[PDB]
Image (cartoon, coloured by chain):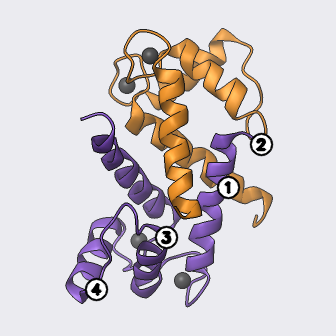
Chain colours: A orange, B purple
Amino acid sequence: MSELEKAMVALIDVFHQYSGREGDKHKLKKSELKELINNELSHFLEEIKEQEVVDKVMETLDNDGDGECDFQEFMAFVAMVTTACHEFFEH
Amino acid sequence: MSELEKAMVALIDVFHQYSGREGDKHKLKKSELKELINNELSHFLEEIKEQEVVDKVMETLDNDGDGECDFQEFMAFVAMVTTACHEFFEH
Ligand SMILES: [Ca+2]
Ligand SMILES: [Ca+2]
Ligand SMILES: [Ca+2]
Ligand SMILES: [Ca+2]
């Protein structure tokens, strides 16, 4: 596999690692999303410690209003973070 | 860096490797996009050999009509392919 292919596999893997913990196995509830950010995005995002921030993150990502983050919504989140990373080598 | 963070970095890196070849260094023209798919997605996508397919792929991905694929458009493409992969381990 190429580096790009390996990256795509890692996205699927980490999503499912967290989504499969509780409830709907194909979606992230707030606690699953919080843990994914805190454990897996610690170099790119400040740790989430406040319920208000958990709530705002889910509200931002949950485009279909079901209170959870599905795979498409997670990929949109990945796109936003990856876009923000540009500041640290271009702008 | 986590597996997720490494994946994000690989997305940025591959996009720029290809986007920086010609013209606008921040966007993929048709030839750059074709080579990215053929070299870097050979296990997930059939090789592109026909101009009609090149054109359709760009037409599908180019949401702002400038005839190129920017980083956001590229991330949308990655999301489509990563979603399609689910068929090979879920249903
Ligand atoms: Ca879940
Ligand atoms: Ca949702
Ligand atoms: Ca270019
Ligand atoms: Ca475009």
Of the residues under marks 3 and 1, which one precedes in the sequence?
1
Viewer-nearest of labels 3 and 1? 3
- Helix, strand or loop for disc 1: helix
**Are both tags, 2 and 4, on one chain?**
yes
Mark 1: give few (<14), some (14-19) or many (20+) Cα within 10 Å.
some
The reply to whether callout 2 and callout 4 are in contact (CB within 8 Å) is: no
- Image height of B18 relative to A80, above or below: below
Q: x, y (%) of residue A50? A: 71, 12
Which residue of the protein is positioned furthest toward the left in this rendering? B52
Marks 2/4: CA distance? 37 Å
Using the image, name the chain to which the residue with label 4 belongs.
Answer: B
Query: Ligand 4 shows up in which quadrant of the image?
Result: bottom left
Marks 3/2: CA distance? 23 Å
The reply to whether callout 1 and callout 2 are in contact (CB within 8 Å) is: yes
Residue corresponding to mark 1: B9
Q: x, y (%) of residue A59? A: 48, 23
Of the residues under marks 1 and 2, which one precedes in the sequence?
2
**Are both tags, 4 and 1, on one chain?**
yes
Ligand 3 lies under 8 Å from the Cβ of mark 4: no
Q: x, y (%) of residue B47? A: 32, 76
Using the image, name the chain to which the residue with label 2 belongs.
Answer: B
Of the residues under marks 3 and 2, which one precedes in the sequence?
2
Using the image, name the chain to which the residue with label 1 belongs.
Answer: B
Mark 2: give few (<14), some (14-19) or many (20+) Cα within 10 Å.
few
The reply to whether callout 4 and callout 1 are in contact (CB within 8 Å) is: no
Using the image, name the chain to which the residue with label 3 belongs.
Answer: B
The residue located at (52%, 76%) in the rendering is B27
Q: Which mark is residue B49?
A: 4
Residue corresponding to mark 2: B1
Q: Is residue B1 left or right of residue B10?
A: right
Q: Which mark is residue B40?
A: 3
